Image (cartoon, rainbow, N blue to C red):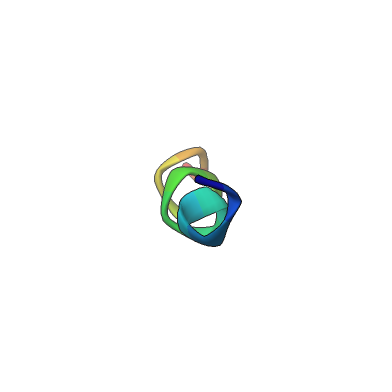
Length: 14
């Protein structure tokens, strides 16, 4: 699933 990691870390931002 790690190809979607960028999508989670984009939602982590403020």
